[PDB]
Amino acid sequence: MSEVNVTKVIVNNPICDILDPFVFTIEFEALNKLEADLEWKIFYISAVNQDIELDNIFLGPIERGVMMFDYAVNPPDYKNMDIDSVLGLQAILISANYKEKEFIRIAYYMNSFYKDMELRENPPVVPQYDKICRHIFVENPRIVKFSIGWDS
Amino acid sequence: MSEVNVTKVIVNNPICDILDPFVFTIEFEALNKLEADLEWKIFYISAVQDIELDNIFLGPIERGVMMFDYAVNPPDYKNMDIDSVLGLQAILISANYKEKEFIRIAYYMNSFYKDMELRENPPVVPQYDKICRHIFVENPRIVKFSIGWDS
Image 1 (cartoon, rainbow over the protein chains, first blue to last red):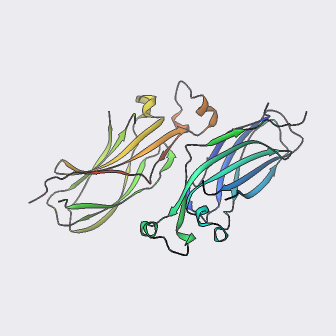
Image 2: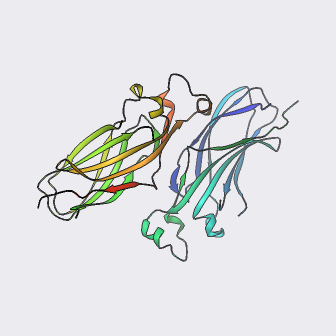
């Protein structure tokens, strides 16, 4: 039923400071030309409280064939977030949409923690976001596909 | 009663193609000068026999702190069981003195196809250039052993 198959997702900087942008290399194959653009979104998932949309971009026109692209998005504003959405188990999710309907989601768990062990053992009362790093679990993508309408 | 303490181990390229060398940064402190060299080995652990990837000698050992980078080449995946290539494996750092092991540090790792179609349908002939390993860095498995030294 799906007109588009996602063939690759590369997490380019799986271990980095949390202030660094998320960078993905994404490959997909269109089985048919589509009249409209594909919409790719990135979501930050907290405290595994609501999901934060990091960015959304449109790609088109969509011809039959394979396309691979780089997608860099900025991190959310950790200063205005619950500390549990900053330190601990989080997730990052790629969402693909057509005509405002999601047809696949790919998410990766990630652990966020202070890089230096003493601050891990004794976290300060005021967080120091410049010394926190995320570790994305690239070997375990969580995928769900959805039946949507396309052009017919 | 150990004369040498291992204070840091950093896995420099924890997520990479399996054909890339393993690179470690290792820090240790000798509480006393030692008459002989330290021997550091790296082992590839299958089906989580073991393959010794390399061994190097460091010396002379003076009292104090030393940090060094240790790069070793991967094993010959073409002559290995596919189950020793894809899946849960391990990589182990071994430190020895006078041919006696006094500490071992190991990390689990998952190795998987980067392309989703080959992940769902792995080929009968492996494509090692398209497999990636993820070394599980925040869970080091350490065991220390009391050995004889110089006294």
